[PDB]
Amino acid sequence: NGTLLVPPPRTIANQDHFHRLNYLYQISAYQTRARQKARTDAHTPLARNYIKSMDLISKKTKTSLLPTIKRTICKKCHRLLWTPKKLEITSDGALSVMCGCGTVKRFNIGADPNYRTYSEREGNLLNS
Amino acid sequence: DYQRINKNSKIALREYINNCKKNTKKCLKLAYENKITDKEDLLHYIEEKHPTIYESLPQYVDFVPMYKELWINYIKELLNITKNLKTFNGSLALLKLSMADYNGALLRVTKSKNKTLIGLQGIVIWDSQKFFIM
Amino acid sequence: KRRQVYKPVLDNPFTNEAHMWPRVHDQPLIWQLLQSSIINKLIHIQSKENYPWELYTDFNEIVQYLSGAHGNSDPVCLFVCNKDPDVPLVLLQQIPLLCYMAPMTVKLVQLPKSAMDTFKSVSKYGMLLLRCDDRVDKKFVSQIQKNVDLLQFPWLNAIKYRPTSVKLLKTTVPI
RNA sequence: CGGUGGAACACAGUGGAGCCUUGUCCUCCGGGUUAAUGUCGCUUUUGGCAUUGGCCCCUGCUCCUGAGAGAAGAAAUAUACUGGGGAACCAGUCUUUACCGACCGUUGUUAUCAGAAAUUCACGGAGUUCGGCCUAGGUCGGACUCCGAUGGGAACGGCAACGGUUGUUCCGUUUGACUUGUCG
Ligand SMILES: [Zn+2]
Image (tube, rainbow over all chains, first blue to last red; front, side):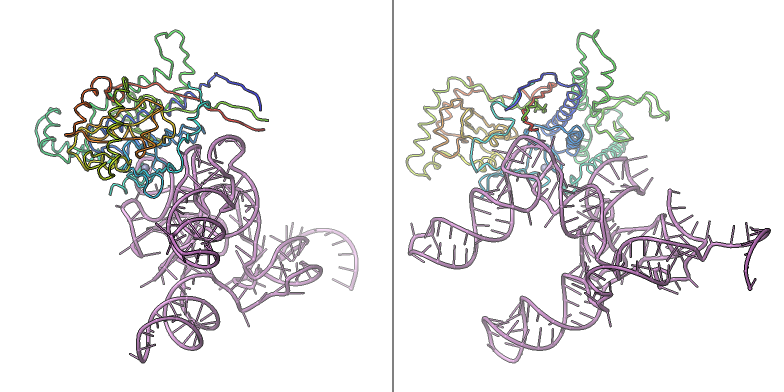
């Protein structure tokens, strides 16, 4: 089919950008969890901001993320869904996950099982 | 009510940083009404007598370990700062700092055109274009 | 001509540790009692499945039960099968997450056997949530849950910086 | 950087030639009222549908031009939408006594992977309505609505080029004063 070339020289600028993205995601998640465990929604427009800036960096470097991150974050307001509104299933569709802002992220789960994403398949992925 | 605030994250952030300043001014007024200079007694005074006013107050004692340890460990990982310091490379480190974000940094105003801005340390909650928020 | 290029993609650095399913051992002593009880429920009458033992086997009822509607029953136990094909992954990446924010003492048990496709093909979906309030079953459920089947969280309990994880995916390019 | 002193208030500043779809006193779409006709249900009569005819619907201001600045209470809290600014606000798309609204059409682009799909191709599932076989309501076809894990994406959304405006295009000046030369 073609040529099989596997390079492990990772580039320094891509490592800098992904460390920046991962640091923003970690600080937003830790703000959200440290606020959520203790008391009510104090600075929930704050951490979301980081995620939004994170996604804007994903516009600049043109990089892609795993569907775990994009499944965690929202699409319109770009907030973390670690505490969502409601989860409904088999309500004449497949699945529905409601949020506080009203934007839902649903999944076709009632069609068939054993469907995996392209990054979750057996051999398509090499860690580190 | 809650849906109309978080329609735009920027405007909700502006409303939050305005509400923190208004709550700080109300805290100064209730602190002069308290006539107690101790802040640890002041926080318990607000918890006893003003429940709704206490809800939007920041917690700096919580803010220091949740930010400083992550920031220092991220810089120790990113700039390759290890126990071996004699293999350092300064130009690529300054290029990485030009590529790294300052969201969550402890930073100090050491020199300024205004004589009152100097001496201020603070941790970033958001980076603006031409101002700075600590 | 096709050429394969490896593209660097940022991973969720803690999803492996957030999906560290709990340590379960000496598990064939448990499926005997569990399967015998579930079959003895499922034999007689579909109303008599749920009159002596109150169990919910629909995920919408699991969310509505853990939302905060019923707060009396504090010890509530859950059984979820992993390492099993024909099981949806979207629910499975959100079942141990939604039980963490529940204020009730919810005890998740991960069943490790791959051959256990019976409970999914028979009852509803392959998961079981029930209450140990005054039932006889708790008289052994409290016995073994302290032994091997402990469920605790190390990942959010202490303060710790997490190292970054950048993986790389395959991409074909035709020219 | 742009325009004026050439156009005399659009008298497209004027003239001539060529071509055609031969310059249609036309048509904005759209919304409201009134009159007439035909069908369908209540039965002095009214209601709904379709056609035809008539009326009504907004120069924000100055200026020849270029341009300049004012305000978005006829649905909002941020004063139409979108993005940023530290806030007065800025940029782009727009409208302005709108007591109804109006983001014009065509072409191409969004590389590679992914996904069913990169432009209302198509495909899969659910619901409704109609027709045929048929009558414990089973199947088939057509139409509509909703959803489908991915990717900045599925949004008639973003970018670039072209005007149907009162037919298009070309050619010429309306710009001079002295000195000299010719002609009457
Ligand atoms: Zn959301």
